[PDB]
Length: 60
Length: 50
Image (cartoon, rainbow over all chains, first blue to last red; front, top):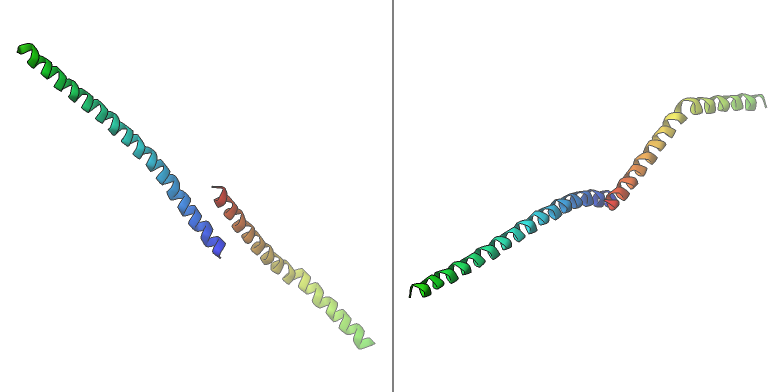
């Protein structure tokens, strides 16, 4: 009976384990996309600051 | 002697009836339980493999 219960628990745990491994896969995909979007955002923001201060220097 | 022969024939008839009618079903139930436990162990092995 313990083996039967353990087999049922193993089936359920492996089902949720494949589900959670997949979910972690999309989670880290979204994480990498978020960091890429960040990197791009702060890079372009620094570029905005640099170009704006260059415009100010040119005006002066 | 004679009563012994009659009783022996009666026992032979009883054994024939048992083997003909009651033995097949009890054997079938035994085999069913064996197959059920075999399937349970195979499913446990399959769950371990999975």
